[PDB]
Image 1 (tube, one colour):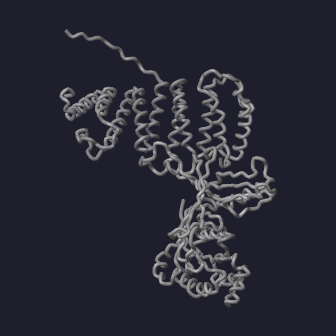
Image 2 (cartoon, rainbow over the protein chains, first blue to last red; image 1 turned 180 degrees about the vertical axis):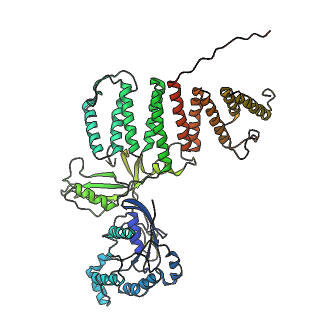
Length: 177
Length: 275
Length: 138
């Protein structure tokens, strides 16, 4: 019986915390109760034996780049995250998140994950991005980013649908396994 | 049949369901069934009816003997059922029957030997808490006992909600999901095209008797967190008030729904309609 | 002393006689003496007087603990005293104290393990009946 370290970072403009809580809550889609605290955890069976795990929820505010790294050491796996519908999130991750995460921990299995996949194909959202001159950036260039790092997996999920979300965590925990 | 009180064929189907649950290794359920059988038995000597004399073996079988043999097997099942509390409960009374009526102390020795193994198991190791879901069957294509009926399923120890959802979908064609998790659908209260919805529920804690203020360890209560349960609540998010941006507690209202089922999980059946 | 109710020195001579009976291996008698000692004890937690705290070992010894330790040793003596009935009698109540108050089930396991050994002994084997005589001193 053992536990697994698992960190998640990302800008505060995507609310990955909602994803994490809705997963751990086993919440019905669009039914999660937002708690007042961070750093969620769960006890998970996937294969062979069940394990514990704690999700290092890290706020993406740039100032906290001095407390985020102290959590990094001895991390089993880290989950880099973004918003599939935010080009600015892409600029952040390829420019700030991915680089400094790679520098702090160049040696750890890594998986990149999309968000608002439901909004990725949302006609109103994509037309708003176009009229605001942002791009509904799609999967293949996400795969290009993955191959750029060679992250052991790249995934795309959503909160209001939880699609592949369970899967997301499955390959996340099987990264060690 | 229990209504019709023809106890013999009742026992026959008891054993049928025992075969089924054993095929599913549902030791808890199988042993509960054998318990239901043993319930009608007494600790008296005289075998009152050969109706309780079944086809497995048939000779004198003093009422006492059949009851104790059943109890023995039930204890075996609880042991491999990882529910040693009930095992202990029946072990005590098997012992007292030995003491007061048969005076065969060798049975005492073996019985309580296993009893020690049980206590060791219960304090020593840890076991996962099974999740519970609320299954609301709706539509009209459902059978009589399923139409517009809500059940609770004692799923596996770590079934994610939609894993069990899919498992049920395998159990049922026309496998769709209504999205208004809380209310039923009045059209679907009569319409065909069976509609269902599933979601995890909160296992309301038990009330361990004589424990309400005792400084007991955690193991006993963790046992009591999952089993011997009938009460179930579900937290209901709601907006009631102004939806100010920086704040949500201007509108947070939780319309929890308690669920009281006829029987106690776990039971002979791994699910039950909410009574 | 029992008349005089100075219980402490009373316990002291209790232990003296225990030493004597042990020297005679009169496990029955020795264990009865320890029983007489344990009689005044309670199953409460608070060690009410350090008078019952003897010289064999001395620290907190919650009343409960001292009583149960005594009971344990008494059970040992009855076992090698070949009088398992009284052993069973005290084993029951040691168990119930465990259940209702300390919740240490390992003690349950070991205690009732010995309890089974006792029942086995009593049904299985046979033991001689001691003779009794009338001694008239004049």
